[PDB]
Amino acid sequence: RFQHVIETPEPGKWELSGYEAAVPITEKSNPLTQDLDKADAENIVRLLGQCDAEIFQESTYQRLYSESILTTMVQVAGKVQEVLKEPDGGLVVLSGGGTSGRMAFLMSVSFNQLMKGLGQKPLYTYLIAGGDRSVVASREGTEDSALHGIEELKKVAAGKKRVIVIGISVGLSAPFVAGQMDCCMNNTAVFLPVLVGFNPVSMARNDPIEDWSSTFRQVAERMQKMQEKQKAFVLNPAIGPEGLSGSSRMKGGSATKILLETLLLAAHKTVDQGIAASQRCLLEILRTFERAHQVTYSQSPKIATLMKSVSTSLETTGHVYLVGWQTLGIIAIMDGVECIHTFGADFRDVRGFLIGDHSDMFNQKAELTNQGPQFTFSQEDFLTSILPSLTEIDTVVFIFTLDDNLTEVQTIVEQVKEKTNHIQALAHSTVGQTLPIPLKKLFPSIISITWPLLFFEYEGNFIQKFQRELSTKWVLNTVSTGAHVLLGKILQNHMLDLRISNSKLFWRALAMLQRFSGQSKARCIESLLRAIHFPQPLSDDIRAAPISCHVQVAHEKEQVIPIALLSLLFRCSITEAQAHLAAAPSVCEAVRSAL
Image (cartoon, rainbow, N blue to C red; front, side, top):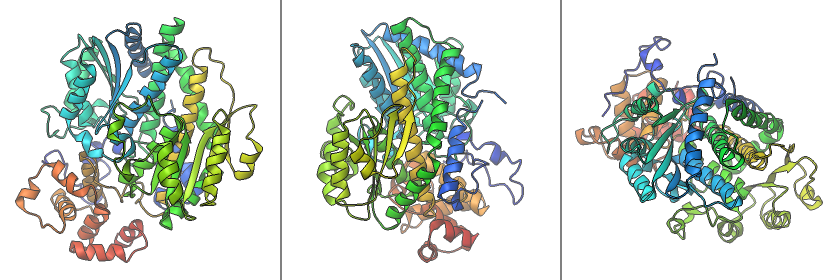
């Protein structure tokens, strides 16, 4: 079970260790954010803003702007336009787990809307590990099954003649995706698999998948072989490590969004305008999203101020609601849910809501209908369940554009204001538009983001929408990450308060123990398993159990890493470690005092 785990390097021998060389780029500590844990709000914005800018940064080897990556994007666009040209029996599937799965969902929503707007039959669908509940709730463990991935692909592809499958896994990690890519390669007469991730192939996970005979790396290596025959594609740009180690939702999610929107827009442009995809045109679009970073981060003071407000509500046991209009609602939903595993947040802490029509977005909306408070997301959910329960300690962030129903925005804001003064808005506008006077009065310090009109004949309106979603993503992700960082929920730039919700998170938790204690792999495994299973003592059956067993027990538990870490550092029992942790003001300070 633990064979792939490398021994902890000896004290002082970390620098050039085989241990450090094997850490995937997606899991690496960013050298610029080692001080993230103790940074103030303004400094967190600068650190996270710098990291977000890194996805665009042109060694030029395998970067997003590299000739190699742009050529792969051109080839994939070529394959997609072949399907768009033949809608009968054609299908474009986007798939993933967690944020990658929610990005697949968003991509399908956006591109089916583009197609509907042009009077064409929609050809996109999404597959998310765990089904529709995973779009709005933390169900990370569902991606650990390759068979689940294959079954969901077989269902949507039934009766189709040509299926493009874009498998999204930032760390080249998700078994759900690996299974799909492998089965696509077994039938190239029907399927064209495209693997999207942000690690070199040699850094893809090589640990065993519980229900599959191939590892992610073996599948990715087979994809490299099929790429020589143009029967598969590996689209893996280099973006560098995340500001918060392994926080794939940030840079990884942003790079997934821009990469896929750019190449898919190019495929649609080929069919509609007759202009084939090119490195030059892909760069023009990508650089528009690069300009969006400068536009967004020019609001750094207000982002920092909002982060403080959100952190205050959380610290007081209040809740934070991100209320977004149309697709900005999807971005809002994606933000809150990630706080659960990342910082050990309760599902009630940060929740996103979509205001507007969501009727043609979900595959199986019945999976969400009256399922419980962990699954709220809609306009009806916000107005009927959240709004009447709002208190003075809660924060509500409103995200909209000046093309939204501003009477409806004003009405909802006023209703919320009766319950709490902790209101703020992120409003996107086109140069020339001004916020109505009642809204300026309700939001005297509004985060106003003004966008020049884009004159791209075909892509103009789509990029306008996409950049506003991306801008919203950066603001909300910096605010939610920062708000939890300010509460001492991280250590250096590592997720100390992480929930072990899937196998990738289990390995990240083990690596963190080895990193922070410097103790042997056997000692770190023993302490991690003891902390997960407590009060159940460790037995040989538990030590030999599959990782899924540890995940199932660990997923609803809080502070597993600091408990396991304090147990290693003090050579104490779990109860003694729990006492040490309870006496401290934060999880960051408890461990810092022990170190």
